[PDB]
Image (cartoon, rainbow over all chains, first blue to last red; front, side, top):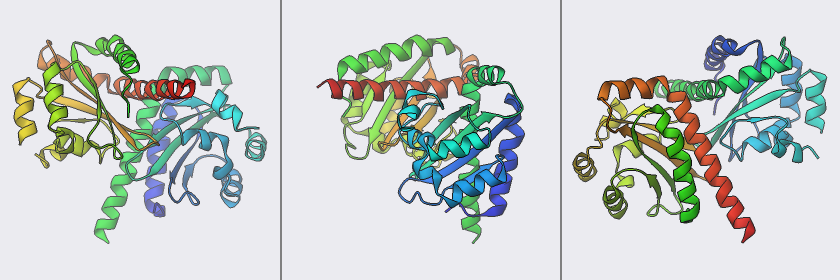
Length: 163
Length: 162
């Protein structure tokens, strides 16, 4: 579905140019078809090794953040009560190993059965100023998710039309 | 079926306190599910019998704005080319109540609902309304998101206590 490497590199540059307005953010943009969810598209500036282990073990299938996002429309912090209940592990060990612990998820569902998430966490920043920046810019970051997804859908429609 | 008038009243309160911050706006919050296509839910401050006729003739099925919203994830104006490219009874009815040049904010959820917040000018002048909707579009999208999250949560609670 979303397997085109050159489009995905354009989307990555699009996200990365705009996400830095909010600080030094680590992010992943994960797009999952909810009827065939085994192979999601992952565009991210997390460490390459994290991404490889996450894909190889299909960790999104047991990731409490992803499992919570599938039932939501509004953004949530990773300590919100819905995330903590599915926590009752392996995905969170991998995350802690790569200093990915404090974070937020913005979610979008579209009319093609896709779920798109923008998951963001602090990298070079203290967690307090990171959290305040996300709390203040929540509406703008959600719009970034919406315009990224819209952009990606248009590029794939355009690429299929050319072929 | 979102039939609880007590919840829908609370949703209406929630929207009107917050939507007034962007000006004197008219709106309809429309939620539809393909499992009940002829019974959509409308929370709105439009003229009451505009709602009645819209609901009566099931105009959401042929409304160019709603048909465009199904392909959208980002907000759009009613005079955008993608709407025009779908543009007659719903048009005529719309003109009678002065619901002319507006904007639509769109949301899909994981229960196969589509929610739209449809917004048009009230008393203000057309230009300041347009500038308002465009400087505040992120906030208004978030208002739709939080309204819908609140409605789902209230219907969830009501079902559990039953």
